[PDB]
Image 1: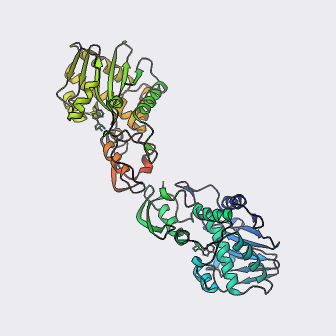
Image 2 (image 1 turned 180 degrees about the vertical axis):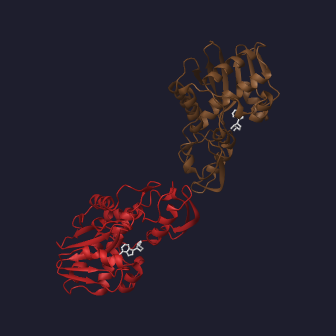
Length: 258
Length: 258
Protein backbone atom coordinates (compact mmCIF):
# COMPACT_ATOMS: atom_id res chain seq x y z
CA UNK A 1 0.00 0.00 0.00
CA UNK A 2 1.20 3.59 -0.75
CA UNK A 3 3.09 5.16 2.11
CA UNK A 4 3.27 8.88 2.79
CA UNK A 5 5.78 10.08 5.38
CA UNK A 6 5.62 13.14 7.64
CA UNK A 7 7.83 14.23 10.51
CA UNK A 8 6.86 16.68 13.21
CA UNK A 9 10.57 17.39 13.73
CA UNK A 10 11.15 20.88 12.33
CA UNK A 11 7.80 20.88 10.47
CA UNK A 12 6.62 24.05 8.69
CA UNK A 13 3.31 25.10 7.09
CA UNK A 14 4.94 24.14 3.82
CA UNK A 15 6.07 20.67 4.88
CA UNK A 16 2.66 20.16 6.49
CA UNK A 17 0.89 21.48 3.39
CA UNK A 18 2.83 19.17 1.05
CA UNK A 19 1.93 16.30 3.33
CA UNK A 20 -1.84 16.88 3.32
CA UNK A 21 -1.69 17.51 -0.43
CA UNK A 22 0.01 14.12 -0.93
CA UNK A 23 -2.55 12.33 1.24
CA UNK A 24 -5.43 13.83 -0.79
CA UNK A 25 -3.69 12.74 -3.98
CA UNK A 26 -3.47 9.18 -2.76
CA UNK A 27 -7.03 9.07 -1.44
CA UNK A 28 -8.67 10.13 -4.70
CA UNK A 29 -8.52 8.83 -8.30
CA UNK A 30 -9.60 11.97 -10.14
CA UNK A 31 -12.32 9.86 -11.75
CA UNK A 32 -15.14 11.54 -9.81
CA UNK A 33 -15.50 15.28 -9.27
CA UNK A 34 -18.91 16.71 -8.29
CA UNK A 35 -19.25 20.55 -8.36
CA UNK A 36 -15.45 20.83 -8.33
CA UNK A 37 -15.14 18.69 -5.24
CA UNK A 38 -13.55 15.23 -5.54
CA UNK A 39 -15.49 12.22 -4.28
CA UNK A 40 -13.70 9.34 -2.58
CA UNK A 41 -13.79 5.84 -4.17
CA UNK A 42 -16.99 3.82 -3.67
CA UNK A 43 -16.64 0.86 -1.36
CA UNK A 44 -18.69 -1.44 -3.61
CA UNK A 45 -16.38 -3.02 -6.13
CA UNK A 46 -13.18 -1.54 -4.68
CA UNK A 47 -10.40 -4.21 -4.69
CA UNK A 48 -8.47 -4.66 -1.42
CA UNK A 49 -5.29 -3.90 -3.29
CA UNK A 50 -6.51 -0.34 -3.52
CA UNK A 51 -8.34 -0.09 -0.19
CA UNK A 52 -5.68 1.61 2.04
CA UNK A 53 -2.77 4.04 2.20
CA UNK A 54 -0.29 4.28 5.04
CA UNK A 55 0.94 7.40 6.75
CA UNK A 56 4.30 6.96 8.49
CA UNK A 57 4.63 9.55 11.21
CA UNK A 58 7.98 10.28 12.82
CA UNK A 59 8.87 12.77 15.52
CA UNK A 60 11.80 14.57 17.08
CA UNK A 61 12.38 11.72 19.55
CA UNK A 62 13.07 9.62 16.46
CA UNK A 63 10.01 7.46 17.09
CA UNK A 64 7.87 6.24 14.21
CA UNK A 65 4.35 4.91 13.93
CA UNK A 66 2.35 4.02 10.78
CA UNK A 67 -1.39 4.84 10.59
CA UNK A 68 -3.64 3.00 8.09
CA UNK A 69 -6.36 5.04 6.36
CA UNK A 70 -9.35 3.50 4.64
CA UNK A 71 -9.51 5.06 1.17
CA UNK A 72 -13.31 5.17 0.96
CA UNK A 73 -13.64 7.60 3.95
CA UNK A 74 -10.15 8.75 5.06
CA UNK A 75 -10.86 7.08 8.40
CA UNK A 76 -7.89 5.92 10.54
CA UNK A 77 -8.43 2.15 10.97
CA UNK A 78 -5.36 1.30 12.95
CA UNK A 79 -1.64 1.68 13.38
CA UNK A 80 1.62 -0.19 13.57
CA UNK A 81 4.33 0.59 16.14
CA UNK A 82 7.38 -1.59 16.09
CA UNK A 83 6.30 -5.22 16.30
CA UNK A 84 2.64 -4.73 17.13
CA UNK A 85 -0.50 -3.67 15.26
CA UNK A 86 -3.68 -2.29 16.78
CA UNK A 87 -7.03 -1.98 14.98
CA UNK A 88 -10.24 -0.30 16.12
CA UNK A 89 -13.21 -2.68 16.32
CA UNK A 90 -14.48 -3.28 12.73
CA UNK A 91 -18.13 -2.34 12.37
CA UNK A 92 -18.94 -5.08 9.84
CA UNK A 93 -17.61 -8.24 8.25
CA UNK A 94 -16.11 -6.83 5.04
CA UNK A 95 -14.19 -4.41 7.17
CA UNK A 96 -13.10 -7.08 9.64
CA UNK A 97 -11.88 -8.98 6.56
CA UNK A 98 -10.23 -6.03 4.83
CA UNK A 99 -8.00 -5.06 7.75
CA UNK A 100 -6.55 -8.59 7.67
CA UNK A 101 -4.50 -7.41 4.68
CA UNK A 102 -2.70 -4.72 6.70
CA UNK A 103 0.60 -4.97 8.58
CA UNK A 104 0.59 -8.65 7.74
CA UNK A 105 4.21 -8.89 8.89
CA UNK A 106 3.79 -7.49 12.41
CA UNK A 107 4.14 -10.19 15.04
CA UNK A 108 1.43 -9.03 17.39
CA UNK A 109 -1.89 -7.98 15.86
CA UNK A 110 -4.45 -6.73 18.33
CA UNK A 111 -7.97 -5.50 17.77
CA UNK A 112 -9.39 -3.04 20.28
CA UNK A 113 -12.86 -3.75 21.62
CA UNK A 114 -13.91 -0.18 20.93
CA UNK A 115 -14.28 1.60 17.62
CA UNK A 116 -12.56 4.73 16.45
CA UNK A 117 -15.44 7.19 16.38
CA UNK A 118 -15.11 10.44 18.31
CA UNK A 119 -17.80 9.68 20.86
CA UNK A 120 -16.09 6.49 21.96
CA UNK A 121 -12.63 8.05 22.02
CA UNK A 122 -13.71 11.17 23.93
CA UNK A 123 -15.27 8.83 26.52
CA UNK A 124 -12.06 6.77 26.82
CA UNK A 125 -9.92 9.97 27.01
CA UNK A 126 -12.04 11.76 29.54
CA UNK A 127 -12.09 15.02 27.53
CA UNK A 128 -14.00 16.38 24.58
CA UNK A 129 -12.56 17.61 21.25
CA UNK A 130 -13.18 21.18 22.37
CA UNK A 131 -10.68 20.58 25.17
CA UNK A 132 -7.85 18.64 23.55
CA UNK A 133 -5.19 21.00 22.12
CA UNK A 134 -4.00 20.79 18.52
CA UNK A 135 -0.67 21.83 17.11
CA UNK A 136 2.67 20.37 16.15
CA UNK A 137 3.63 19.88 19.82
CA UNK A 138 0.47 17.84 20.56
CA UNK A 139 1.08 15.74 17.43
CA UNK A 140 4.75 15.19 18.40
CA UNK A 141 3.57 13.88 21.74
CA UNK A 142 0.87 11.69 20.20
CA UNK A 143 3.38 9.84 18.08
CA UNK A 144 5.28 8.89 21.27
CA UNK A 145 2.18 8.00 23.27
CA UNK A 146 0.98 5.80 20.37
CA UNK A 147 4.45 4.34 20.04
CA UNK A 148 4.87 3.49 23.76
CA UNK A 149 1.48 1.90 24.03
CA UNK A 150 3.14 -1.07 22.33
CA UNK A 151 5.62 -1.32 25.23
CA UNK A 152 3.29 -0.99 28.22
CA UNK A 153 4.32 2.66 28.47
CA UNK A 154 1.06 4.49 27.59
CA UNK A 155 -2.23 4.59 29.51
CA UNK A 156 -5.61 4.01 27.88
CA UNK A 157 -6.82 7.66 28.23
CA UNK A 158 -3.62 8.91 26.65
CA UNK A 159 -3.92 6.46 23.74
CA UNK A 160 -7.45 7.82 23.07
CA UNK A 161 -6.43 11.47 23.40
CA UNK A 162 -3.55 10.79 20.97
CA UNK A 163 -5.80 9.26 18.30
CA UNK A 164 -8.20 12.23 18.56
CA UNK A 165 -5.24 14.47 17.74
CA UNK A 166 -3.91 12.33 14.87
CA UNK A 167 -7.34 12.00 13.29
CA UNK A 168 -8.08 15.76 13.23
CA UNK A 169 -4.64 16.70 11.98
CA UNK A 170 -4.59 14.08 9.26
CA UNK A 171 -7.99 12.77 8.19
CA UNK A 172 -10.01 15.85 9.03
CA UNK A 173 -7.45 18.16 7.48
CA UNK A 174 -7.41 16.07 4.31
CA UNK A 175 -11.21 16.33 4.03
CA UNK A 176 -11.57 20.06 4.68
CA UNK A 177 -9.36 22.82 3.29
CA UNK A 178 -10.82 24.87 6.15
CA UNK A 179 -9.48 22.55 8.84
CA UNK A 180 -6.12 22.12 7.13
CA UNK A 181 -6.01 25.92 7.20
CA UNK A 182 -6.49 25.98 10.97
CA UNK A 183 -3.58 23.58 11.40
CA UNK A 184 -1.26 25.63 9.15
CA UNK A 185 -1.91 28.62 11.39
CA UNK A 186 -1.14 26.67 14.59
CA UNK A 187 2.13 25.57 12.99
CA UNK A 188 3.09 29.03 11.71
CA UNK A 189 2.77 30.70 15.12
CA UNK A 190 3.71 27.57 17.05
CA UNK A 191 0.39 27.84 18.83
CA UNK A 192 -1.26 24.86 20.42
CA UNK A 193 -4.99 25.27 20.85
CA UNK A 194 -8.22 23.40 21.07
CA UNK A 195 -10.46 23.53 17.97
CA UNK A 196 -13.26 26.13 17.93
CA UNK A 197 -16.95 25.40 16.99
CA UNK A 198 -16.38 25.88 13.26
CA UNK A 199 -13.84 23.06 13.13
CA UNK A 200 -16.01 20.74 15.26
CA UNK A 201 -19.25 21.34 13.38
CA UNK A 202 -17.51 20.65 10.05
CA UNK A 203 -16.13 17.43 11.52
CA UNK A 204 -19.59 16.44 12.68
CA UNK A 205 -21.23 17.35 9.36
CA UNK A 206 -18.89 15.77 6.78
CA UNK A 207 -21.32 12.95 5.91
CA UNK A 208 -24.44 15.12 5.78
CA UNK A 209 -22.65 17.68 3.58
CA UNK A 210 -21.40 14.89 1.32
CA UNK A 211 -24.97 13.67 0.88
CA UNK A 212 -26.55 17.12 0.52
CA UNK A 213 -24.09 18.08 -2.20
CA UNK A 214 -24.43 14.79 -4.04
CA UNK A 215 -28.20 14.96 -4.01
CA UNK A 216 -28.58 18.67 -4.61
CA UNK A 217 -30.65 20.09 -7.46
CA UNK A 218 -28.08 21.74 -9.72
CA UNK A 219 -26.18 22.52 -6.51
CA UNK A 220 -29.18 23.69 -4.51
CA UNK A 221 -29.87 21.89 -1.23
CA UNK A 222 -33.46 20.69 -0.65
CA UNK A 223 -33.08 21.65 3.00
CA UNK A 224 -30.34 23.90 4.46
CA UNK A 225 -27.53 22.64 6.63
CA UNK A 226 -26.74 24.72 9.72
CA UNK A 227 -23.06 25.14 10.64
CA UNK A 228 -21.24 27.42 13.16
CA UNK A 229 -18.79 30.27 12.79
CA UNK A 230 -15.59 30.41 14.87
CA UNK A 231 -17.46 32.67 17.30
CA UNK A 232 -20.14 30.04 17.86
CA UNK A 233 -22.89 31.68 15.79
CA UNK A 234 -25.06 29.56 13.48
CA UNK A 235 -24.77 29.93 9.75
CA UNK A 236 -26.99 28.23 7.17
CA UNK A 237 -25.73 26.61 3.96
CA UNK A 238 -28.16 26.48 1.03
CA UNK A 239 -25.82 25.94 -1.88
CA UNK A 240 -22.65 23.92 -2.59
CA UNK A 241 -21.06 27.14 -3.78
CA UNK A 242 -20.03 28.45 -0.38
CA UNK A 243 -18.49 25.08 0.43
CA UNK A 244 -16.28 24.73 -2.64
CA UNK A 245 -13.33 26.38 -0.88
CA UNK A 246 -14.12 24.65 2.47
CA UNK A 247 -14.56 20.97 1.74
CA UNK A 248 -11.82 19.08 -0.07
CA UNK A 249 -13.13 15.50 -0.35
CA UNK A 250 -16.50 13.84 -0.08
CA UNK A 251 -17.42 10.31 0.94
CA UNK A 252 -19.25 8.45 -1.91
CA UNK A 253 -22.99 8.76 -1.24
CA UNK A 254 -24.48 8.21 -4.67
CA UNK A 255 -23.80 7.95 -8.40
CA UNK A 256 -23.92 11.23 -10.28
CA UNK A 257 -27.10 11.86 -12.31
CA UNK A 258 -26.87 12.50 -16.07
CA UNK B 1 -20.95 57.75 -27.49
CA UNK B 2 -18.86 54.61 -28.30
CA UNK B 3 -19.54 53.21 -31.73
CA UNK B 4 -19.13 49.56 -32.69
CA UNK B 5 -19.31 48.68 -36.39
CA UNK B 6 -20.46 45.44 -38.03
CA UNK B 7 -21.06 44.57 -41.66
CA UNK B 8 -23.17 41.70 -42.90
CA UNK B 9 -21.16 41.77 -46.13
CA UNK B 10 -18.96 38.67 -46.05
CA UNK B 11 -19.58 38.12 -42.31
CA UNK B 12 -18.24 34.97 -40.60
CA UNK B 13 -18.80 33.40 -37.16
CA UNK B 14 -15.53 35.02 -36.22
CA UNK B 15 -16.42 38.53 -37.39
CA UNK B 16 -19.84 38.10 -35.77
CA UNK B 17 -18.25 36.76 -32.57
CA UNK B 18 -15.80 39.66 -32.32
CA UNK B 19 -18.72 42.02 -32.79
CA UNK B 20 -20.88 40.63 -29.97
CA UNK B 21 -17.79 40.44 -27.76
CA UNK B 22 -17.12 44.15 -28.38
CA UNK B 23 -20.72 45.10 -27.62
CA UNK B 24 -20.60 43.22 -24.29
CA UNK B 25 -17.35 44.99 -23.47
CA UNK B 26 -18.93 48.36 -24.04
CA UNK B 27 -22.13 47.55 -22.15
CA UNK B 28 -20.40 46.51 -18.93
CA UNK B 29 -17.85 48.17 -16.62
CA UNK B 30 -16.41 45.08 -14.94
CA UNK B 31 -17.31 46.70 -11.63
CA UNK B 32 -20.13 44.24 -10.89
CA UNK B 33 -19.93 40.48 -11.35
CA UNK B 34 -22.44 38.24 -9.53
CA UNK B 35 -21.75 34.45 -9.62
CA UNK B 36 -19.40 35.01 -12.57
CA UNK B 37 -22.04 36.83 -14.55
CA UNK B 38 -21.61 40.57 -15.21
CA UNK B 39 -24.41 42.92 -14.23
CA UNK B 40 -25.25 45.94 -16.37
CA UNK B 41 -24.87 49.48 -14.93
CA UNK B 42 -27.65 50.68 -12.59
CA UNK B 43 -29.84 53.39 -14.02
CA UNK B 44 -29.88 55.40 -10.78
CA UNK B 45 -26.90 57.70 -10.77
CA UNK B 46 -25.74 56.83 -14.29
CA UNK B 47 -24.63 60.03 -16.12
CA UNK B 48 -26.05 60.55 -19.64
CA UNK B 49 -22.52 60.71 -20.94
CA UNK B 50 -22.30 57.01 -20.24
CA UNK B 51 -25.90 56.02 -21.00
CA UNK B 52 -25.60 54.72 -24.63
CA UNK B 53 -23.42 52.98 -27.20
CA UNK B 54 -24.02 53.00 -30.94
CA UNK B 55 -23.90 50.07 -33.29
CA UNK B 56 -23.27 51.05 -36.92
CA UNK B 57 -24.58 48.33 -39.18
CA UNK B 58 -23.61 48.19 -42.84
CA UNK B 59 -24.57 45.70 -45.50
CA UNK B 60 -23.58 44.43 -48.92
CA UNK B 61 -25.74 47.06 -50.64
CA UNK B 62 -23.43 49.57 -48.97
CA UNK B 63 -26.24 50.93 -46.81
CA UNK B 64 -25.62 51.94 -43.21
CA UNK B 65 -27.84 52.49 -40.21
CA UNK B 66 -26.85 53.23 -36.58
CA UNK B 67 -28.80 51.64 -33.70
CA UNK B 68 -28.67 53.19 -30.20
CA UNK B 69 -28.55 50.79 -27.23
CA UNK B 70 -29.40 51.81 -23.69
CA UNK B 71 -26.51 50.62 -21.52
CA UNK B 72 -28.63 49.70 -18.49
CA UNK B 73 -30.58 46.96 -20.41
CA UNK B 74 -29.05 46.49 -23.89
CA UNK B 75 -32.40 47.61 -25.32
CA UNK B 76 -32.47 49.17 -28.82
CA UNK B 77 -33.96 52.65 -28.29
CA UNK B 78 -33.79 53.95 -31.81
CA UNK B 79 -31.78 54.35 -34.96
CA UNK B 80 -30.34 56.87 -37.37
CA UNK B 81 -30.49 56.44 -41.16
CA UNK B 82 -29.08 59.24 -43.23
CA UNK B 83 -30.69 62.49 -42.16
CA UNK B 84 -33.44 61.12 -39.94
CA UNK B 85 -33.69 59.60 -36.47
CA UNK B 86 -36.49 57.40 -35.16
CA UNK B 87 -37.09 56.55 -31.48
CA UNK B 88 -39.53 54.10 -29.95
CA UNK B 89 -42.02 55.73 -27.56
CA UNK B 90 -40.18 56.40 -24.23
CA UNK B 91 -41.93 54.73 -21.32
CA UNK B 92 -41.09 57.47 -18.80
CA UNK B 93 -39.77 61.00 -18.46
CA UNK B 94 -36.10 60.29 -17.71
CA UNK B 95 -36.01 58.15 -20.79
CA UNK B 96 -37.82 60.71 -22.92
CA UNK B 97 -35.16 63.15 -21.68
CA UNK B 98 -32.19 60.84 -22.14
CA UNK B 99 -32.83 60.08 -25.81
CA UNK B 100 -32.68 63.83 -26.50
CA UNK B 101 -28.88 63.45 -26.28
CA UNK B 102 -28.73 61.03 -29.21
CA UNK B 103 -28.22 61.80 -32.91
CA UNK B 104 -28.40 65.45 -31.98
CA UNK B 105 -27.12 66.37 -35.45
CA UNK B 106 -29.75 64.55 -37.52
CA UNK B 107 -32.14 66.97 -39.18
CA UNK B 108 -35.33 65.00 -38.74
CA UNK B 109 -35.94 63.41 -35.35
CA UNK B 110 -39.12 61.38 -35.10
CA UNK B 111 -40.56 59.46 -32.19
CA UNK B 112 -42.79 56.51 -32.96
CA UNK B 113 -46.08 56.29 -31.10
CA UNK B 114 -45.41 52.67 -30.23
CA UNK B 115 -42.71 51.20 -28.02
CA UNK B 116 -40.08 48.68 -28.91
CA UNK B 117 -41.24 45.66 -26.93
CA UNK B 118 -41.80 42.38 -28.75
CA UNK B 119 -45.55 42.26 -28.25
CA UNK B 120 -46.05 45.61 -29.92
CA UNK B 121 -43.65 44.86 -32.76
CA UNK B 122 -45.07 41.39 -33.48
CA UNK B 123 -48.50 43.05 -33.70
CA UNK B 124 -47.25 45.72 -36.13
CA UNK B 125 -45.38 43.07 -38.21
CA UNK B 126 -48.21 40.60 -38.40
CA UNK B 127 -45.98 37.64 -37.42
CA UNK B 128 -44.59 36.21 -34.22
CA UNK B 129 -40.90 35.68 -33.32
CA UNK B 130 -41.35 31.97 -33.94
CA UNK B 131 -42.10 32.80 -37.57
CA UNK B 132 -39.57 35.48 -38.49
CA UNK B 133 -36.34 33.93 -39.85
CA UNK B 134 -32.92 34.77 -38.44
CA UNK B 135 -29.59 34.64 -40.19
CA UNK B 136 -27.14 36.90 -41.97
CA UNK B 137 -29.47 37.19 -45.00
CA UNK B 138 -32.40 38.40 -42.84
CA UNK B 139 -30.11 40.89 -41.09
CA UNK B 140 -28.74 42.14 -44.45
CA UNK B 141 -32.29 42.80 -45.55
CA UNK B 142 -33.24 44.49 -42.27
CA UNK B 143 -30.50 47.06 -42.64
CA UNK B 144 -31.99 48.07 -46.03
CA UNK B 145 -35.60 48.04 -44.84
CA UNK B 146 -34.61 50.21 -41.85
CA UNK B 147 -32.56 52.42 -44.13
CA UNK B 148 -35.34 52.95 -46.74
CA UNK B 149 -37.96 53.72 -44.16
CA UNK B 150 -36.30 57.14 -44.03
CA UNK B 151 -37.06 57.62 -47.75
CA UNK B 152 -40.68 56.48 -47.92
CA UNK B 153 -39.44 53.14 -49.24
CA UNK B 154 -40.35 50.74 -46.39
CA UNK B 155 -43.80 49.72 -45.11
CA UNK B 156 -44.74 49.70 -41.43
CA UNK B 157 -44.94 45.86 -41.12
CA UNK B 158 -41.51 45.52 -42.67
CA UNK B 159 -40.01 48.14 -40.34
CA UNK B 160 -41.35 46.11 -37.35
CA UNK B 161 -40.17 42.76 -38.73
CA UNK B 162 -36.72 44.30 -39.30
CA UNK B 163 -36.39 45.57 -35.72
CA UNK B 164 -37.39 42.14 -34.36
CA UNK B 165 -34.47 40.71 -36.33
CA UNK B 166 -31.94 43.37 -35.29
CA UNK B 167 -32.90 43.10 -31.63
CA UNK B 168 -32.48 39.30 -31.42
CA UNK B 169 -29.22 39.28 -33.35
CA UNK B 170 -27.70 42.11 -31.38
CA UNK B 171 -29.24 42.75 -27.97
CA UNK B 172 -30.43 39.22 -27.28
CA UNK B 173 -27.18 37.71 -28.49
CA UNK B 174 -25.20 40.08 -26.28
CA UNK B 175 -27.24 39.02 -23.23
CA UNK B 176 -27.13 35.26 -23.76
CA UNK B 177 -24.13 33.21 -24.84
CA UNK B 178 -26.74 30.60 -25.76
CA UNK B 179 -28.49 32.86 -28.26
CA UNK B 180 -25.23 34.20 -29.69
CA UNK B 181 -24.38 30.54 -30.21
CA UNK B 182 -27.53 29.97 -32.27
CA UNK B 183 -26.63 32.89 -34.50
CA UNK B 184 -23.04 31.66 -35.06
CA UNK B 185 -24.49 28.38 -36.30
CA UNK B 186 -26.88 30.10 -38.72
CA UNK B 187 -23.92 32.06 -40.08
CA UNK B 188 -21.60 29.05 -40.36
CA UNK B 189 -24.03 27.00 -42.46
CA UNK B 190 -25.62 30.05 -44.09
CA UNK B 191 -28.93 28.87 -42.72
CA UNK B 192 -31.81 31.23 -42.17
CA UNK B 193 -34.31 29.96 -39.64
CA UNK B 194 -36.86 31.04 -37.12
CA UNK B 195 -35.83 30.74 -33.45
CA UNK B 196 -36.93 27.61 -31.56
CA UNK B 197 -38.62 27.60 -28.06
CA UNK B 198 -35.31 27.66 -26.17
CA UNK B 199 -34.29 30.96 -27.73
CA UNK B 200 -37.75 32.51 -27.19
CA UNK B 201 -38.16 31.41 -23.59
CA UNK B 202 -34.71 32.81 -22.72
CA UNK B 203 -35.70 36.09 -24.37
CA UNK B 204 -38.91 36.16 -22.37
CA UNK B 205 -37.18 35.26 -19.09
CA UNK B 206 -34.14 37.58 -19.06
CA UNK B 207 -35.57 39.87 -16.36
CA UNK B 208 -36.89 37.09 -14.13
CA UNK B 209 -33.56 35.24 -14.36
CA UNK B 210 -31.68 38.45 -13.58
CA UNK B 211 -33.79 38.89 -10.44
CA UNK B 212 -33.72 35.24 -9.36
CA UNK B 213 -29.94 35.14 -9.61
CA UNK B 214 -29.46 38.44 -7.83
CA UNK B 215 -31.75 37.44 -4.99
CA UNK B 216 -30.70 33.82 -4.70
CA UNK B 217 -29.48 32.29 -1.46
CA UNK B 218 -25.82 31.49 -2.15
CA UNK B 219 -26.94 30.82 -5.73
CA UNK B 220 -30.04 28.81 -4.84
CA UNK B 221 -33.36 30.06 -6.22
CA UNK B 222 -36.25 30.38 -3.73
CA UNK B 223 -38.59 29.14 -6.44
CA UNK B 224 -37.54 27.41 -9.70
CA UNK B 225 -37.76 29.03 -13.09
CA UNK B 226 -39.17 26.86 -15.89
CA UNK B 227 -37.55 27.17 -19.33
CA UNK B 228 -37.86 25.10 -22.56
CA UNK B 229 -35.46 22.91 -24.49
CA UNK B 230 -35.06 23.26 -28.28
CA UNK B 231 -37.56 20.41 -28.64
CA UNK B 232 -40.20 22.31 -26.68
CA UNK B 233 -39.93 20.33 -23.43
CA UNK B 234 -39.95 22.15 -20.08
CA UNK B 235 -36.86 22.24 -17.95
CA UNK B 236 -36.61 23.67 -14.44
CA UNK B 237 -33.75 25.85 -13.18
CA UNK B 238 -33.02 25.75 -9.44
CA UNK B 239 -29.50 27.10 -9.32
CA UNK B 240 -27.48 29.83 -11.07
CA UNK B 241 -24.89 27.18 -11.85
CA UNK B 242 -26.57 25.78 -14.94
CA UNK B 243 -26.99 29.30 -16.29
CA UNK B 244 -23.39 30.45 -15.98
CA UNK B 245 -22.57 29.32 -19.53
CA UNK B 246 -25.99 30.47 -20.88
CA UNK B 247 -26.51 34.02 -19.69
CA UNK B 248 -23.87 36.64 -20.43
CA UNK B 249 -25.24 39.85 -18.88
CA UNK B 250 -27.87 40.69 -16.30
CA UNK B 251 -29.99 43.81 -15.89
CA UNK B 252 -29.34 45.51 -12.48
CA UNK B 253 -32.06 44.31 -10.09
CA UNK B 254 -30.47 44.88 -6.70
CA UNK B 255 -27.27 45.66 -4.81
CA UNK B 256 -25.18 42.66 -3.87
CA UNK B 257 -25.43 41.56 -0.21
CA UNK B 258 -22.29 41.38 1.95
